[PDB]
Each structure stands twice: as structure tokens, then as C-alpha cells.
Image (cartoon, coloured by chain):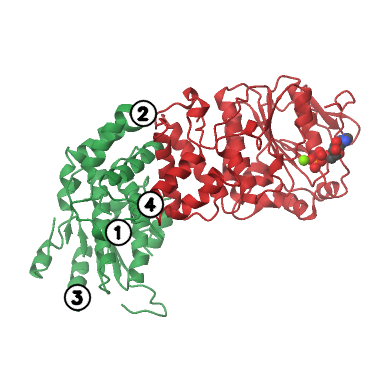
Chain colours: A red, B green
Amino acid sequence: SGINDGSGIVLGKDRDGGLVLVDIWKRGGDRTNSNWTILAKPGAGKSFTAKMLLLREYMQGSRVIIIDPEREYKEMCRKLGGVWINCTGGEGKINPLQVRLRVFQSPLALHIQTLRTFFSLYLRDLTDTEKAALEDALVEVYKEAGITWDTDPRGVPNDKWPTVKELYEYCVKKAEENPETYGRLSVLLKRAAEGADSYLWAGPTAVEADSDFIVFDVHDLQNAEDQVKRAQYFNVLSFAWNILERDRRERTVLVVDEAWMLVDPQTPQAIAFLRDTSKRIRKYNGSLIVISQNVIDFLAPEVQRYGQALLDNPTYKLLLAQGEKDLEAITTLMNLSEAEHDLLVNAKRGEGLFVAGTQRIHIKIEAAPYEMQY
Amino acid sequence: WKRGGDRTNSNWTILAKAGKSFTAKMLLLREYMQGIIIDPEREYKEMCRKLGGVWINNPLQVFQSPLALHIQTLRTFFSLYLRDLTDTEKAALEDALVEVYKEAGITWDTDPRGVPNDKWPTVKELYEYCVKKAEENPETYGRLSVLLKRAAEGADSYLWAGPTVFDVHDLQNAEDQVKRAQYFNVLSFAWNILERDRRERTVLVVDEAWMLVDPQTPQAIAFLRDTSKRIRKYNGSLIVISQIDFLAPEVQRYGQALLDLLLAQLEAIT
Ligand SMILES: Nc1ncnc2c1ncn2[C@@H]1O[C@H](COP(=O)(O)OP(=O)(O)O)[C@@H](O)[C@H]1O
Ligand SMILES: [Mg+2]
């Protein structure tokens, strides 16, 4: 039906053949944030459209950060000289116990809660006594490394942080006097310290991640256990978010792809973390783009308080062809008309509904031939 | 004392502007003759003595870790006493608790049934701990120490800084946070009495309960409701007597379940 801001980027075409031109940095009326939700079944053109939009923003000066479970952004990253991070290779190790930047608030306390979320995703049946023994072992393992409550993360070198190894070893030592509080905790933690999952976390953060185009590839976890997927994705999202605070460049775009992977009904704090990120990022004048299939996953009773805001709050939305369950979930959530329902029903590749504030239109996405090399 | 049908619990709620203390004490002597009161107004001192029972005028005294949950009740006692505590300061305090305990040689796996009231650490050692921590962590510990001073070796230290009708009246004109705090503590110690000796059919009166209402720490109230549900689980009776404080938006979730005899009043209870 037509959406043309004076300037910005061209996203695709009208139903009448007119260019849809959108400036996602606008503020005013129904443009309250710069955030996107991109929802569709596999193969509908989600990653492609994202790549086109990111390319066009990057060209204008946006730094771009991407979490990439499908390995869809590697090539584009090469073409732009970006930093490509192999989060499963030793060279891409991201230490979860590396405290992340935030009247006065203790960086350490903040990061201990983050870890509650992190260790709940990875260890799913942790009792309340273990939770707090773990939070205690955490602070203690920090102390022994010379980091304390006032300590400023910005000044600490990557290798001074403790790892899950020290945490696991402290838990074993404690198990002696406390076999019942720590016993089962220590053993579960071994897997991450020395065992099958240690390649991910048992060492210092390997990378700086200073570039205007970063991608965290987590592709090598596609066949790993769910809890490993989820715990690594959350660690990576937390590391990635820290980059915006660490050096608050404006118009940064943070892209979390296949975001459904983060959903854990028993630990909705991970999606809350995502929800909070979309809120905070407005302050830094950036953009959170959430890309996903499996929409209903967000809308589950345990996570829906969080998921629902995550997906419906963003000023810009792109809905392409949907899975049957997902389409009914979306039609209800975003009050799609009947026309808008059917549009997405027979929607062809790269075609669907584009939302900007309260403006919703039929759109067909298409990239210029000179861009295709990306 | 009944059960079944419409008789689910043995709780009471006496509300009014009216003689709730009279009525309460009479029926108390009454249920008694067939055989634990928090009294901030000395309304049972004389009666308690006429019964010749016992009248008396350490919060740090404590699979599931006895320590790990006494740590939570503790975080409430402390939110009540220190009103402007930051999340960081709260966490700092909690950790301090754990460490002060470790130095007293009590851990996560320790049976609290084996520690003399003397072996427990007190608020003094928590203060000394924090003062020490505050040298390297002033941002996180400085104010927490400056604030714990009056409770360790200052104007409140008499209340807690030693190894441990419950008369509260001596704090009737103190700061409301202090009185709210002690009320909370005594309430803890009493509930402990009645979760240590399962002498059934016990009544625990909470006189003027609104004193334990802090819109910013509705936890003390949550604890009230908890005690009210638990006591049934030990075949007993909680009695809350009070003169809207319980129905306020931030406490109501607790105070509605809690508050559900009516004397002179009103609009809210109608
Ligand atoms: N608008 C488009 N024009 C041309 N090719 C497209 C378009 N959208 C997607 N494709 C291609 O079709 C395939 C599916 O798109 P993709 O974004 O990977 O799907 P998904 O929705 O699963 O992320 C990709 O190989 C991509 O190159
Ligand atoms: Mg995709």
C-alpha cells in the first residue's frame, strides 16, 4: 500500500510496483524504536532479506553484530573484511565467567545473575540449594582470581578471569565437607570443565571482537544436546551485547538469528535477557533484529510474558510464508486482518507483510544484482 | 480446631479500630484452659503473669541447606532494617553472611541441631567482616558497614549482638524500620519454637500485625502468610489482630490471603 520515508534504504517493492524506502533510525509517531522481528518458516527468505538489509545499513555506517547458527553470514563477513568468530573452535572460545560490563552497581553481582540463567540452561534440574551453593562457589572462585565486588571489568585481562575449570575444582574441594550441597553439583560441572563440553568454555576468551562487522558462528552446535545449544547461544548473546556497552558506537545492529534456540520453558530468563536487550539497545541508539522460525516457541506459557513483548514490540516487522501453527499464532498476536492472513497464506518466497510502526503492507523483497555477490 | 467441610484451618483475623485486645485475651485464656504471643503493646504481660507462665522482653542463628534458606529470611530481616539497600548491596550482604558463617565453622552441610547458641556468629562479626571487605570494596561495602555499625556496636546492638508473651513494646517510639525489623525477627524465632517442637494445637498471636507491613518489603508479610499455611500443616493456629495496609497494591498479593472477628471500624472490609 506504500511506505516511503524520505530517505534510508530500499527494502523492496509495493503491491503497485513502488519502492518501499525505510529509515529505521527515525524517531517520531509510531517509530519508537529501531528494532526488527523477522518471522517465517524455513526457506521463505529470512536470512537473505536480513543480509540485504544489513548490507545496506553497513554501507551507511552501521556496525553489525550477528549470532549465526546456520552459517549464513560467513561469506558476507569475508567480503566485508569483518571478524568471523568460530565459537566452537579454540580460536573462538568465549569464557562465560568473564564478567560483562553493566547509582553504583557491582559488575560482579550483575554477572552472577547472568550466570544463574547460564547455568540453569546448561544444568536444567538444579535445586535451590545448589543454585545458591553455585552462586557462592562463583564469588569464591572470583575472589581467588583477584576479582572482587568493586573490580572494573574494563581493566582486567582476558586471562585473569577464572573459568569453569576453577569453578568445578572448587566445587569438588567443597564436596568433601559438603557432599550433599555440592556433590552432585561438582560432578555435573566436570562435563564442562574437562569433559565432552569443555572445548566450549574451559579457558580464556580468545577474541577481542573489535570490528564494524562481527559474526559469532555457533553452527557446530546444530546437533549437540539442547542445553548446550541454549547455554552457548546465551553466553554468546551476552558477550555480544557487552560489545555495545564496551564502546557505545551508534546505529549498531545486533542480529540474533534462529532466536527460538534460546527459548527454554524452564529458564525463560534467557528470553527475558533478550527482551531487556531490545529495550536497552534503544538507549545506545542501536537496533536489535530477531530472526526466527518456530514462532509458537516464544508464545509458550512459561516464556510468553517475555517472548510476546520481544516479538511484538519492535517498530519494524517482516512476516513471510509461515508454518500452519505459527501463522495462527501470529494472526492472533499481531491482529492480522483476514486479507493479511491469506496474504501470508499464499505468500511466495521473499513476499509477505512488512510492518513499520502501525503501517502494514504487502511487500516483495528483491536485491540489486551488484549486491548478490554478498 | 475443627476440620473438614467449611472448616479448612484454625486461623483467626481480629480487625478493628474497639477492644480487640480484650476479646483476644479472653478467648486466649479460654483456648488455653484446654491445654505464644507477639505483643508490641504489653497487653498480655499482666495476664501472662496471672497465668504464671513465662514472660520475656540473635538473627544470625539458623537435600535442602538450613543455611541457604535462613539466608533468605535473613535477606528480609535486613531489607526491613536497611530500607535503601541496593541489589548490589543486598548481594554483598548475603555473601558476607555465608563467609561470616564459614569462619564460625558452619557450612552448607551442617546440622544446626549441633551448634550452641554461642557458636553461631552474630551481627558483630558480620559488621567486622564488612568493615574489612570495605577497605578494598568501598563501592560495594562502605555504606553497608557504616549502616551495620549501629546494629553491631551502636544504638541497636543490644537487640541482636549476642548469642540469643514476647514483649516488643520497648521499641514503640523507635524508628519504624527497627521495630518492623525486630518484629520480623521475633516472629521468626517464635515460628522456630513451633517448628522445632511439634506440640500440636498451638496458637501464635500476632498483635498489631500492620507493623510488619513494609510496602517496599512485602516479604515480611509473605512470611506471615507462609506461617499461616504451615501451622495448619502442624495442626495449629495463627491469630493476626490488627487496626488497608494489608490491601496495598504491593502487599495485597500477600495481605489478601493473610486477612482471609470484626469490631468497630472498614470500607475495604465491607
Ligand atoms: N528475495 C529473494 N530473491 C532471490 N533469492 C532469494 C530471496 N530470498 C531468499 N533467496 C534465496 O533462497 C534461499 C532461502 O532463503 P533464506 O533466507 O536462506 O531462507 P530462511 O527464510 O530459511 O532464512 C537462499 O539460498 C537465498 O539465497
Ligand atoms: Mg534463516
Crowding at mark 4 (Cα within 10 Å: few <14, some 14-19, many 20+): few
Q: Residues within 10 Å of mark 3 (few under 14, many from 20)?
A: few
User: Where does the C terminus of chain A fall, quadrant-wise?
Assistant: top right
- Residue A71 is marked as none
Please indicate whether residue A249 sits to the left or right of residue B5 in the image: right
Disc 4 is placed on an element classified as helix
Give the alpha-carbon distance from disc 2 to disc 1, as whole Å. 35 Å
Q: Which residue is mark 3?
A: B30
Tell me the distance, in whole angstroms, between the alpha carbons under discs 4 and 3.
Answer: 53 Å
Q: Please, what is the three-letter code of the amino acid marked with disc 4?
A: Glu
Q: Secondary structure at mark 3?
A: helix
Marking on residue B139 = 2
Q: Earlier in the sequence, mark 3 or mark 1?
A: 3
| Chain under callout 1 | B
Q: Which mark is residue B111?
A: 1
Q: Earlier in the sequence, mark 3 or mark 2?
A: 3
Label 1 packing within 10 angstroms: few (<14), some (14-19), many (20+): few
> Mark 2 or 1 closer to N-term?
1
Real-space Cα separation, disc 3 to disc 1, in angstroms: 38 Å
Against A54, is B179 above or below? below
Q: Picture coordinates of residue A34 (x, y %)?
A: 67, 31
Q: Are marks 4 and 3 in contact (CB under 8 Å)?
A: no
Q: Nearer the viewer, mark 4 or mark 3?
A: 4
